[PDB]
Each structure stands twice: as C-alpha cells, then as structure tokens.
Length: 376
Image (cartoon, rainbow, N blue to C red; front, side):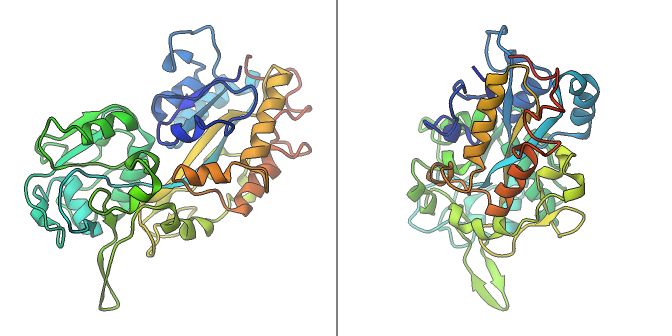
C-alpha cells in the first residue's frame, strides 16, 4: 500500500471513500509538521508505530522551507528523485466560537486582530455582536498548516496592534509580545482537539479559534450560522457600511480563480507551486482579496516524482489523473467537505508537469526515474 498522512485540515476529505484511489492506505491525520517530517525523512513513526512501513506522500498546509527543500535535494533526490509539492484544494480559514446570542457575530479585520493579539479581551468589544464577557482563545499546540495559513493573514493585515504577528506553524510563537497578553489561552492538538476544546460544555462560554472549514461546523449550512461561526470583513467601503462574509467556500472561490499560475520557467522548483497570500500583489505573492471572505489559502500534496515500485507509480499517476482531471475528478467531494476546487488552468498546469509522460517532471518518467525512486 501507498502510505500518506499529515495535515488535519483536509483529513476528512482524504478519508472520504474514493477520493484517494486504488492502492492508497487510509490517510493518517497528524498535523502538517509531522507530515513534512514523515515524507522528507521517510519516518513513518510520525504516523504510527509500524515503522517497517515507508512513507509515500504527505498532506501539508505548511509550505516546504528552504532548508527542507535543500536537505531533500542533497540527501534524498539522487536516489529517490525530485519531490513534488502541489496545491490540492483551496480553503478558507473559519472562526468558530462558543458564545450565545441572537445577533450575528461579524468581525472587522481590526477586531479579529485584537481578539488574537489579546487587545480585545471581552466580547463587548465586538461591535454589533450583542455579547459580553471574557473571550478565551484556543489555538493549535503543535506545528500546524492551519496556523501557517492563519498567521500569514495576521502578518499581512494586523498592522496596528502593539506587536506584530510572524508567519509560523506554531501559534504560540507568532505574536511578537508572546501569548502573555492573552488570559488563559488554551492549546490543543489537531483540528479535532481544538474543536473538542471549543465545544467543551464543562467550561464557561467564550471560546474562539481559527479552523478548517470542514471542522468548523457539523455541516456546510452551519458555516453560515453567524451565532456560531463568525463572519469576517465588517467595515466601511466607499462611505457605506458593509457586512463581512461567512467562510463558506462560495465566498473565497472568486479570489482563488484568479491566482496566477506558477512561473513556467521555474516549475522545476517546488516552492513556486504553492501560492501564498500577502498584503500586496508582487514578486509571486498574491494580495489577500478585498472582496468576499478575506482569510484563505491552499492546502497541498507532497509526492515523489519516482517510486521504486512500478505498480505504486501507476497508482500515484491514477490518483493525479483523478484529483487534477478535467472530468471524473474529486471536485464534488472537495465541495462537499467545505473546500474550493482548483481552477481549471491550475489542474491543467499540474497535469502538464507531473502527468504528461514527455515532461521531464512527470511522475514515473522512464528517463528520469531509471533506476531510482522511493522505497515501496
């Protein structure tokens, strides 16, 4: 079997029957940090105790770092082939909370920033929410791609707090002044662990967090309940008050559709395949959108170009053919789990590099993978 795991943000998608195709073992959700280690170092111990198994792929919503890429290129690539890093689906980052009230909770970006910096410690500081009492932040204890996607937004947009947020996979390391300004912030492990803490009725109401939209509510409809999942984007544009949007996929799809393709000449560099958002467009960075739901990003796949086993090679190719297909694809399942399919031009680009047999980057390319590949 082909073994993968990593990011919890999309784990329920990858666990849905037939999203992963023949040969793929059930996906093991353990966090993006562990997913990257598992793949880069071939350490199945990050997935489970049966370390006779080899790792074949990972899900991650944390980008591979310069050091990770360079180390793999030097240590593993000569014998195993190039790694491949590609977007899987696009996603919002939802803000679920436990605080009763008939009023819609609609955070301005400034309010969001204050909640997560500690500047706003009481629900009464959220205009229009009709709520009062302490806010308690729940965050991911471990190295998390959800944290990376969220802190990338805070870094770009929270520009008038006392401190600043660094982009990181460890939330406790993000704010320059630390977590100390927050009173009783709670760390939990996994998307599921954070939601369990958020939903814990043995403690007082008031908790809030950042979350995969597939976990942030029991069903898609729940993402539109602003008494449980915050709208984000409240403000004033051209002199007129505007409401924020829910993190429903429909509210980020327009922004995703116009994300530029990875620069053609550099498509041999895995770093260019994962777009990141930022304050302004330029140098490969895509500006966070001024319309729709504001907090978005990509979750990604990490594979090898080459596998020692020919059956596994074909099975990986069959998965790419489905996941990036023009038709007979995973898009209905992607949408059903609160995510945004990749645009057609993105699917085509992924296929043209990693599937089309003649391409030097293609999975199982006979000239490149001659005598090479990750162990079965």
